[PDB]
Amino acid sequence: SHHWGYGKHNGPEHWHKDFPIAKGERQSPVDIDTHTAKYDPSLKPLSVSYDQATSLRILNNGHAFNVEFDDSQDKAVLKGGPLDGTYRLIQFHFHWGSLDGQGSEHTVDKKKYAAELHLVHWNTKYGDFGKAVQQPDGLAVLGIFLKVGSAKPGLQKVVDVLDSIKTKGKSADFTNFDPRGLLPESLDYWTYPGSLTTPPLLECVTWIVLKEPISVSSEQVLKFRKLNFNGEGEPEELMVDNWRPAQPLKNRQIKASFK
Ligand SMILES: [Zn+2]
Image 1 (cartoon, protein in one colour):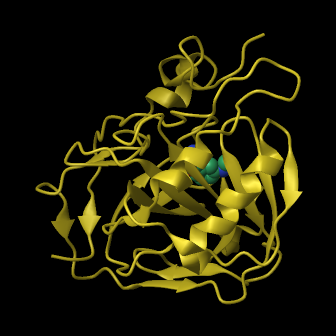
Image 2: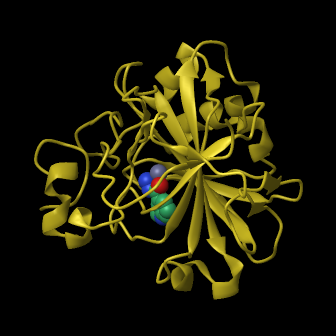
């Protein structure tokens, strides 16, 4: 049967048939043109409070892998930056390529990074994630580019569990993971209003994309590429190129926290 994905017959160019908002006015990702983004001195420093984060599980959902967190209290939150109020971390995941020259969803002056990390947070004034994704300010996604170079120590625990969630629907306990180990040195960022980059493509996201990429080793990203989109007992389809390309900016402004 038919299901959205990243192949020739069900990839991003087809999604609009199931999810018409794919052609909407606030779709993500976008290209970040550094000569059109404007420094905004009213933007605050980003406040990342992850000390009390409680990771729970890692899941291969057939499109990527999600590391899930306990979001029943303000244990890992994002405040400040462009945001009003408090956004709780619910999960993170990555998008990556079959080759080092592709994989990111956002681009910077058309440059594509090897991968991109998305830390997904929801606005606590809406009570739960499901209600937050019915609101134009329901979500905040922190996006972090990955380039291939030196290894990222804080990523290694993720890499070393992937063998246990090779196929769609597999999960593994994944407690005591500290997402601070995935951050770059600088928290300078670009921000713009957009959407989920996977179906249902809902236009609920304040995007906060960090300027500084993190470095991961070739071996770390190679291990991402050994995952499978398929379920156990089905033909093997490597989980690679699970990225949506840049979408039209339309009537949107990208602001920079730095000059
Ligand atoms: Zn994503």
